[PDB]
Length: 138
Length: 137
Ligand SMILES: [Zn+2]
Ligand SMILES: [Zn+2]
Image 1 (cartoon, rainbow over the protein chains, first blue to last red):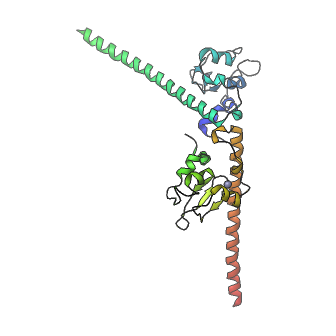
Image 2 (cartoon, rainbow over the protein chains, first blue to last red; image 1 turned 60 degrees about the vertical axis):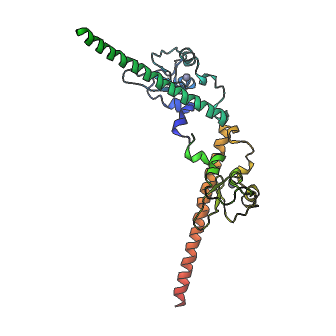
């Protein structure tokens, strides 16, 4: 078997992350198809259909039965390298594989960074408003 | 950033295991050379030059400066699959790699087994002698 950190590169693992996925036989966005497109299922109490690309970290919910996950991935995250990987996992060279895993580690940092920015800016607006209000109480 | 279990497949890791190795520049069995041939350094108080193939688990000590580790590996463990791997690590496919790692896992078991056999036979010798000594009476 393989290290936990790398399991998501495996289609079978990705599929196994969907336990109560609602869209099964009859639907375009099945687990096989969500997984082939790179998604993991990471449902919340608030969004029980939330999926994430394991590679670029894009999150999507609001899935409908006729939705094609490849098309949707390609719409919301056109830059994602995974969409270029033509080869099956075992046909990859370790060099190719390690190269992918560095891009994924960069994409993860970028996601954490872009989050911290947003939270920072929300905080900064509160503090600015609070000080503005006090200068005004005048 | 690779899993501890798999590091020994990397030449630079293998070299790093040689800290107190006596045969350095000028010698045929340097760390670069020991490492290229598959060896890790696993010295004991009793055998400070003990080296082991990471892949087939063969152990060798009694190293001399003109010794070529590939030639020694071939001589004592001719069956070892690692001696066939012509490609650099990164040029391997994951399939090829996973295939190698299963063979290594089998080799390890076989060695644990060949150890347990030897310990068993040593214990049996002791018991035999003990019964012999008493029966002399
Ligand atoms: Zn993606
Ligand atoms: Zn060997």
